[PDB]
Amino acid sequence: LWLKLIFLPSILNRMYFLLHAEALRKRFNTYLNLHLLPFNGTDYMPRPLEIDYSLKRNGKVKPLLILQKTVSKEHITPAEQGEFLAAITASSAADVFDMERLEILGNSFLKLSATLYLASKYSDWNEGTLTEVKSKLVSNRNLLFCLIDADIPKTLNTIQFTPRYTWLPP
Amino acid sequence: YDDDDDNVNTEEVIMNFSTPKVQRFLMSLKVSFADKDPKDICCLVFVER
Amino acid sequence: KNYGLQHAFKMLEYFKICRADIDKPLTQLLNLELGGKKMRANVNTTEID
Amino acid sequence: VTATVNKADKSKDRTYKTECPLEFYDALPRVGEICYAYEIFLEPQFESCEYTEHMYLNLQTPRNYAILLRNKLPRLAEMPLFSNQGKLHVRVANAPLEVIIQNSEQLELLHQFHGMVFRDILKIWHPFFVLDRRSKENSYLVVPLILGAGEQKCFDWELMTNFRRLPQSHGSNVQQREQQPAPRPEDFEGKIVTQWY
């Protein structure tokens, strides 16, 4: 029991942010009306977290997966709780995963979506002002404000776990 | 010749090759701040020379 | 990564990054219109060729 | 967005009031209410060997601890931990243990043991820490478990009524060691000892 209690603070600190990730997962699934699916309903089976081994301290064209599941719904996969936890966990928290790899795809999608939205909305503008407005939309300040007003930064995992020094037990 | 582990060998040599004044000082230091938070302690040592 | 672009477009409505409208929903950005006065759809293809 | 004054300080940051998960809020168990305990199971992944026999064997013993809440947890993903002997797998049981606390002193014993673990076994304690009864943010308990009747498990009351605080390690001189009873192997098997000399 002493050996098992040695690991207790780490387990509790992971459970904290796993519960935050579950909250985010359920909230986003419900907002998309996808919460009634067999995958995402009461029968959700969370897959175990996966080690991101890329981290430093750890004839024919193949169809693209995201586009494959964009047009056909049979390839839709449940949004994993571990994936949301990785999205929340910053690199400063010296955990075994971070938000870096997801951020690349998220940034690319945000840029593409803002570009198409502005092009469809303001089709009678020159390229210069469209580029400027897009740079404003995807700027750090805009994303910062529009995530602060979503009450997300109160649930982020961004500090290294030093239980003895900067941690308050339950 | 006592052992090969240097980390405890330093403690051993310090404990053997010091007068009981230094030994008792170090032991009182160890038992005073065994596993505490460095921000939780603030101490002074007054010596003459 | 989990739901494709069509569902991911709705998230920008959640974060208020892209303001929605009755005429152009966010789910239909894949239906981009190269509209405006800059295009002339009545021109016969011989002039282009 | 018009003003350009705030474009210089690209390296700013802000202070945010953190908030616990909704489950952990107001999760302190109460007398005469149903509370749920989720046992924590540790699965050692590394292959057993002469160096890692103790860590492999001990972690598989069914004397685990749980986490005690008023609120009900969702299903949690299995999680990896890296001990010095290798990798670990930790899972939280999806089916909670449902019990009721019918004694204020019983709850006091539970919460005293919870405070004891951090104060002594893990030494997380600080001079200003206080045992919290406010039943507010981040308030839940940790309780040990032992096998009872059948496959069901229960609270391990004897350890908590015995270990309110860890006894301080004190040596014995020859005089007082003489009449101390002869040590028995059963009293040392699977226990914790320390070299006081």
Image (tube, rainbow, N blue to C red):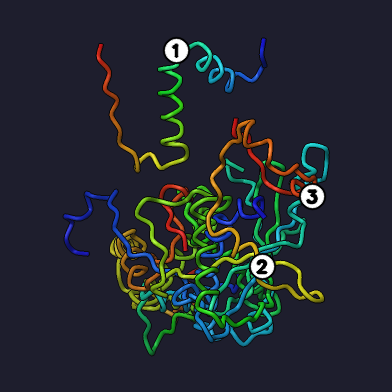
Find residue A93 and name its label.
none
The crowd level at tag 3 (other Cα within 10 Å; few <14, some 14-19, many 20+) is few
The structure residue drawn at horizontal position 34% and vertical position 54%, both measured from the top left corner, is D128
Find residue D156 and name its label.
2
Q: Which chain is home to disc 1?
A: B
- Above or below, A148 against A59 in this view is below
Viewer can see residue A164: yes
Question: How far is mark 2 from mark 1, CA to CA?
Answer: 50 Å
Amino acid marked by disc 2: Asp
Q: Residue D155, percent across and down?
A: 65, 71
Residue beneath disc 1: B19
Q: Nearer the viewer, mark 2 or mark 3?
A: 3
Amino acid marked by disc 1: Thr
- Tell how many labels: 3
Residue beneath disc 3: D186
Residue B43, quarter of picture: top left
- Helix, strand or loop at mark 1: loop
The crowd level at tag 1 (other Cα within 10 Å; few <14, some 14-19, many 20+) is few
The structure residue drawn at horizontal position 57% and vertical position 72%, both measured from the top left corner, is D68
Q: Which chain is home to disc 3?
A: D
